[PDB]
Length: 333
Ligand SMILES: NC1=N/C(=C2/CCNC(=O)c3[nH]ccc32)C(=O)N1
Image 1: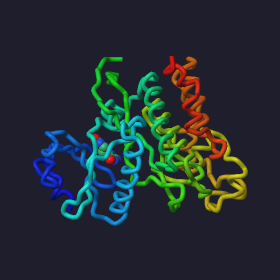
Image 2: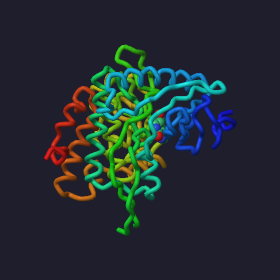
Image 3: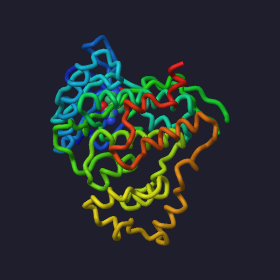
């Protein structure tokens, strides 16, 4: 098992000495190592489960990273830099530049308090620019979520408001290219982590780059509030939540979908008065009611979020367009 080969002091590839665990995911774990053959540089090594689906994803991730890193050698577009890969007791191991905490882990260690708006703006711009670079290279990420956006450096100051932690420097990088898909490749029927999953994915209408834009809109709401507006583990409940927050689904999408299981005639097959129904009614409300302030900068953020959460993936704002939105005009002064 992986536990046997991922401990502090273990040495990988006769080169990388484990000093700490950074994180764990479905794929395996990421450890911090000292690289004895690169002057003692600390690096991150992703140790992948010796399990078919995760091995395949790792091999695909390596191919994507080779492409992206050769295309953008200066990391101008802020995708994580892969250094090399190797195999260790049957596990694929991928070596990366060492980053700070994921945006998820930062929020968690901050008592699930949200980020300040000025930080959200800077983070959103960088996320959009980075994912737009993928989109320009015929790729879709498919698994954008706060766990896959990492701070370059996660030092903070703390002060009483709740005691809150505030980032010194909110610069990010995008990680995890194990699900990333090229335009001409097979598209998995299911993609994304549930809370960040686009309606065209749920309804099996076909997906491409716009599903990343949806995920980004969900991420920005979580950064703003400290929690998801879609607190569910069920697809039909997820659609019910979308309806309460964003309004009814477009007729044409309901007309076209093979996912007839979710619908009674032309409307969601949903009992407002069941346990799940009562929960959705309590937990969900129109998007703009989640605003914490009516100051114009909040209005600018919510205008962008609403465009990112457009149901129709063709109408949905692209990242190239998002980068020109008024919310970002403050960064361009
Ligand atoms: N999910 C995912 N996380 C990755 C890395 C590798 C990139 N660098 C890191 O420091 C790191 N810290 C915590 C996790 C990571 C990664 O490559 N995929």
